[PDB]
Amino acid sequence: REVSSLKNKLRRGDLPFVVPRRMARKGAGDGSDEEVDGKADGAEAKPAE
């Protein structure tokens, strides 16, 4: 039973294997025309003493 079990393991291929995984694709998507200006207001605080 021990020799038979060892022979069946080699014939079946029982080994510490890992299922492979595929690769992901890049998300290079086209942009939209929703542009915003970089304008900003100025400060109005007074200097300290």
Image (tube, rainbow, N blue to C red):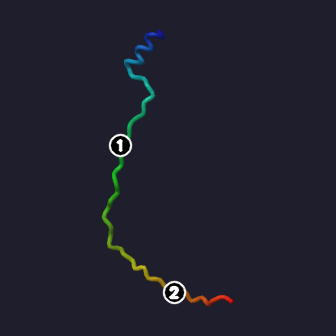
For image coordinates 39% across by 22% down, the residue present is: 13
Numbered disc 2: secondary structure? loop
Mark identifier at residue 42: 2
Q: Quadrant of the C terminus?
A: bottom right
Calculate the distance from the C-alpha at mark 2 to the C-alpha at mark 1.
52 Å
Viewer-proximal residue among 3 and 45: 45
Residue 11: % across, % down:
37, 18
Viewer-proximal residue among 38 and 34: 38
Q: Quadrant of residue 31?
A: bottom left
Of badges 2 and 1, nearer the viewer stands 2
Q: For the residue marked with disc 1, what is the amino acid? A: Arg
Mark identifier at residue 22: 1
Residue 2: % across, % down:
48, 10
The mark nearer the N terminus, 2 or 1, is 1
Up-down relation of residue 32 to residue 37 (above or below): above
Numbered disc 1: secondary structure? loop
Up-down relation of residue 23 to residue 29 (above or below): above
Q: Quadrant of residue 28?
A: bottom left
- Residue at the extreme front of the image, as rendered: 49
Residue 5: % across, % down:
45, 14
Mark identifier at residue 35: none
Q: For the residue marked with disc 2, what is the amino acid? A: Gly
- Residue at the extreme right of the image, as rendered: 49
For image coordinates 40% across by 15% down, the residue present is: 8
Pointer 2 local density, CA inside 10 Å: few below 14, some 14–19, many at least 20: few
For image coordinates 38% across by 20% down, the residue present is: 12
For image coordinates 42% across by 18% down, the residue present is: 9
Residue 18: % across, % down:
42, 33
Up-down relation of residue 26 to residue 14 (above or below): below
Pointer 1 local density, CA inside 10 Å: few below 14, some 14–19, many at least 20: few
